[PDB]
Image (cartoon, rainbow over all chains, first blue to last red; front, side):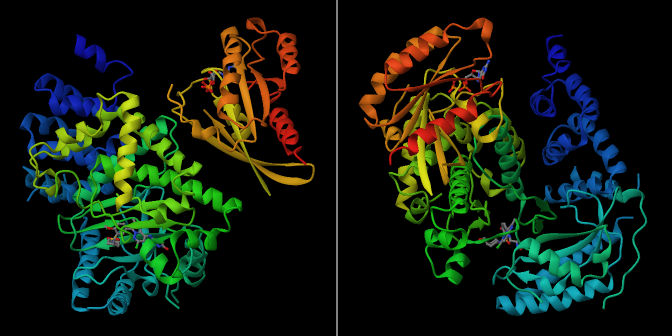
Amino acid sequence: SWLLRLFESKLFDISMAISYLYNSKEPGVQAYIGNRLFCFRNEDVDFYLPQLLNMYIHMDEDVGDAIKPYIVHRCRQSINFSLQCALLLGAYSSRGTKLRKLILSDERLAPEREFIKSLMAIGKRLATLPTKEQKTQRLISELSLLNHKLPARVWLPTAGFDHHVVRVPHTQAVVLNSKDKAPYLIYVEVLECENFDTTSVPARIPENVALKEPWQEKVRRIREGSPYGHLPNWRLLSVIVKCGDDLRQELLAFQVLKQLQSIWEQERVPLWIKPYKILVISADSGMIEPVVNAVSIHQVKKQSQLSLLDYFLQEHGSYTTEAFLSAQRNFVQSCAGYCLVCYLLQVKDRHNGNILLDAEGHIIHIDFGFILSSSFKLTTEFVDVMGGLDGDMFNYYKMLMLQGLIAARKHMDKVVQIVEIMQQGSQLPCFHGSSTIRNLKERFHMSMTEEQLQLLVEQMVDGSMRS
Amino acid sequence: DYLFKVVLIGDSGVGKSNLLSRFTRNEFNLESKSTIGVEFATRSIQVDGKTIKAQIWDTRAITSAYYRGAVGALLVYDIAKHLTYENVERWLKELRDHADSNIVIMLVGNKSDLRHLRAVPTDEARAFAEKNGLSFIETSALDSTNVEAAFQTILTEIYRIV
Ligand SMILES: COc1ccc(-c2c(C)nc3c(NCCNC(C)=O)cc(Cl)nn23)cc1S(=O)(=O)N1CCC(CO)CC1
Ligand SMILES: Nc1nc2c(ncn2[C@@H]2O[C@H](COP(=O)(O)OP(=O)(O)O)[C@@H](O)[C@H]2O)c(=O)[nH]1
């Protein structure tokens, strides 16, 4: 009864459920929890979908059979849910196949699956164009052909809500680098739904310049030009398309960032970070929901020809202005946040090509390749913005890191769970070691005293400055 | 225009952090996560026709550096906990060792709403208050009767450097 006691208490959440499901060898508990999944809010359980599906594949049939009923139910009440399952099911198997074929089958998704295939197809073709600008022009043309098929039964799973895609402002699309299988950013027009699953696809509305501009300014320009723009139903979305890059590690980092965000949210630590949504489509390819009002450090330095501090003063005002001190504050909090993330996940390959700066002054790390077992920099440019090593704002940066560390420890188990389950039957480079998760736990330093942690924060920072 | 750095000091529990959230975010909370080291918060006001911005720092291990460059310090005790008032003597010997010898200080009795639990009489405090060179007031972050007054007083008092 001691087990059942816990499970019937308020303490029981989807987190606890998954932990026992993953670890417990008792078939009576597994089945009991399988049923208990239904009582939880769809949104809360949704977050753990990658974990659940992983268990299904790599764990005992008993465990799968406990998971299956809930999954099928959701798939049956939401094609969005169905889609994400099928995509994840496929990606994480290269046991899976039986359910994947069965889920996509009736128990019509062709429009969506063909829609997605074309986007991938486009990207692969751009490989023959060795320059950024050439790719962009080829993209725009080929995107226009998409428009010929615009009003159709498809949606963007990366969207917070259900909807229909109406229009692609192809002229606005841009390619983000010169690489062989370069990713590309596109803007998409949609009409919001109350529910996709019960609603007729909208009717076509007949077609009658791209420059560097803020997001809200970009919506205006696009809206005024758009056929559907008059409608109140109309909204503009955006996604990045990666045709040849694995996003499974990227997804894992996302969950961790979201958890760490919640941890720091539950506690009262004013660290700042920005998780960006991830969509695994294959082990090859995925999509990303981009941050608006932000651009790379590298390009910030190429148009301004300035140093980071100089750019802040130009773009916000002198250190005596409110806008600057606010921006500085947003900078410092975002630096401490991402430092901790980099350390905990052991993120490498850190350079100014991989750090974005938003319009409020936050920095944002993006490339979570090279983490954990697979084998962060505090440059003086960064230290200058903080007012220098003797600066109060810099001292605060160190203060936040400690605070955010103490917070993380209080919820350590929530974090490791996400990673430890994912390691299952895994061939991801981040799991190459024998002790990937074990080393991860050591990095929380649960044994350390706070005085010891103060010292550890200092040690971390000294390392971060050498470059 | 100006930039005034102010610190909040006192025994743990006296109410510094809620004072800060009331005055700067007009927010209060009964549930409390302990402050690890230091916080600031900022809000701008006008005194005698001039736009000022106040930077308040809410403070075991003690980096004496944060005391540096503070024009004003609010020294707070809990009216309902005599010991917190008792340690006000030890909190003033510290501040003269590690802080500007010509700094504006306000003594603050917080939680004045707890009338029936009062352990420190207003007269005894203000007596000690004007017996020394500190300005004095009692606040309730909970009811927020004297919180605005306190800052604007000390900030006005401060600007009085010329
Ligand atoms: C997987 O790596 C990421 C990660 C994040 C983003 C991203 C998000 C979520 N949001 C934005 C973003 N926001 C600006 C949106 N503009 C608007 C809406 O006006 C601008 C930019 Cl460059 N990246 N980005 C893009 C890519 S990437 O694969 O495309 N590639 C990787 C290689 C280089 C890394 O350094 C350049 C970026
Ligand atoms: N009754 C009452 N209690 C307060 C008031 N302000 C703070 N407290 C309580 O006393 C504690 C003291 O403030 P705290 O947030 O710990 O900041 P610290 O005292 O500087 O560490 C708070 O956690 C509250 O529970 C108030 O105005 N009235």
